[PDB]
Image (cartoon, rainbow, N blue to C red; front, side, top):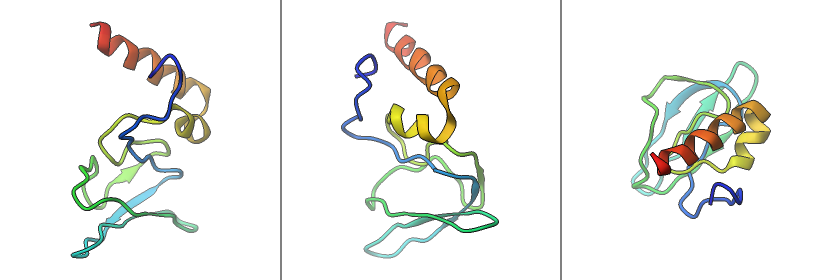
Length: 97
């Protein structure tokens, strides 16, 4: 899955830009706002999904919000080549180790 650069089947959502996390939990919804100084994008997730972020936390661009495998391509647009190289080499080594 790593050597072929495939979007994982159960994949985590990563933040596109910087901001601070503001949680919203409805009975039927679990939207998450990452709020920057200019404007902000909203990510709607399944209700039972696991989160890595406490509320009101500062998240860099390309930081996993969800638990799951990162899509290497989403990461390439957000963080640039060196960040993807870091992710691939370590994630491969995880299995072999």
